[PDB]
Image (cartoon, rainbow, N blue to C red):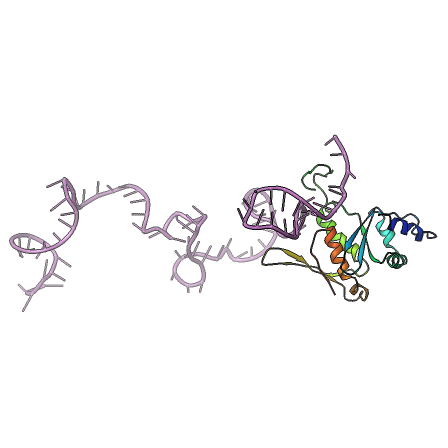
Length: 163
RNA sequence: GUAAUUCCAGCUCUGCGAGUUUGCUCCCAUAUUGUUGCAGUUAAAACGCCCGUAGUCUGAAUUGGCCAGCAAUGGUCGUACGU
């Protein structure tokens, strides 16, 4: 894109903390109400972004007319597929399950999660059902659809988000 | 054990039939040897108790979701970019 990359470098002027931060990539989504932007960060840089963060995110969200959900590059295969490098034994962090669950605790950062579950249907198909802490939002109440779109892009999963 | 529906005989009747009883061994009947598949409060059957090695046994977790299904499969979401 370089909508967010141009937007970040101008607001990064004058700040010691945001001085060395970088963005790899971004994926826009269809959110019914507005759109949402999902901004990937090089892993070691997550807690550098995420230490303060809430200074600049209102300024970035207001300018682009969209919500911003910051995410780590969490990547993870047991069987070689080619075009990828795979550890034989592998590691828990490396595996997909850790990746998909680490992704949530980025996406909805500031509230954190009380409950999580699945609902398996009579047909067979499955619906994840995350529950946000009932204390942080307040704010979380406003952006629920945005996450359901955004999380369905990254992991492929039909979720909902509730109190 | 002097009235024998079981003895000893006759008569009638029954079975199987060029076959038919009688011994011993052996399988089934028998979940009465139990992998399938027994039983152990009182019928036979839970060590007097604890440690404990050989032995048998050993919680969850690791590449999927979504659509066309009648399956084989084939697309999309994820790009994780080694030889």
